[PDB]
Amino acid sequence: QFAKPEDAVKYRQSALTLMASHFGRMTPVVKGQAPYDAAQIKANVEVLKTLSALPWAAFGPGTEGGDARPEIWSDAASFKQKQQAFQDNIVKLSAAADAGDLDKLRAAFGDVGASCKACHDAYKK
Amino acid sequence: QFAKPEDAVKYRQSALTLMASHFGRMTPVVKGQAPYDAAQIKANVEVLKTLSALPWAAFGPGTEGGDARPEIWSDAASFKQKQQAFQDNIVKLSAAADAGDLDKLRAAFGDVGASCKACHDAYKK
Ligand code: HEC
Ligand code: HEC
Image (cartoon, rainbow over all chains, first blue to last red; front, side, top):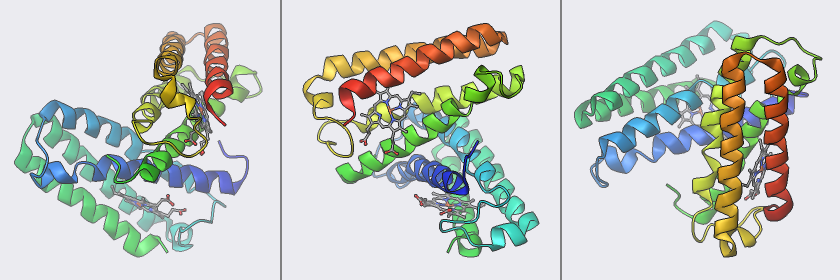
């Protein structure tokens, strides 16, 4: 869907920005600093899970650029591993949100965050 | 969800960028220059309809900035009108995609695009 590789970089960056907002805005709720409204969280996690699937298709062949490390493309198997692991962690967060369980939401949220950081430490400049 | 107003501007810009990609990438299919795979379009329109709901909440009070015209906030009723009209047009596009009907997809896609342009001509610098 990208006319030039830069278009793919801007796309991915925009997706990750939105993930990020939808992930991070739940921090105060996981920490108990904001109230827990199960329905509000369920609906937000449903936005996050749609968004969480989007960045990956925008690291296709020849879309080197941005703050992506080249290793994304020389170590493709490892990178697909780490995105699929992240997405699997999002499934667990969606299950927790769907159950309306603040303890399981907290644990799941931490799992997800560790998966963001694990990818970044290997693949983000 | 925004620590400062700039965070809201970057969010909205990122959302609109992603709408945009998910909208525009269907142009060749509406024009017949790429093949029509009903399932592929149905799934893409489902991403677009989630994305299409996101920018509006990031033009809250005091989030002036970006390429947003001030009229967004002095003419709030008009702006909510134009976003709700746009979203209603997205409903019609989702119905067309769900029906697997290329004629209705084409008409709906044009409706949607006119709603993007109508907002921009009033509210985007
Ligand atoms: C888990 C929820 C997250 C969160 C909150 C973010 N990411 Fe990542 N990310 C990855 C790479 C390769 C990039 C560089 C992309 C590029 O510049 O080309 C990034 C970038 C980001 C950003 C910055 C986006 C920007 O606006 O420029 C942010 C906000 C961000 N990430 C948040 C790689 C990955 C992963 C590899 C499998 C995974 C998993 C994540 N990121 C997860 C998350
Ligand atoms: C219909 C599908 C679309 C499409 C393809 C886009 N928009 Fe708009 N838009 C609106 C305003 C006020 C802004 C300025 C936002 C800001 O800078 O603060 C924009 C911006 C955009 C962009 C640029 C984003 C960027 O990366 O900076 C693009 C790509 C874009 N739009 C595409 C206002 C509206 C509407 C008001 C109700 C509606 C409807 C749309 N936009 C619709 C669409």
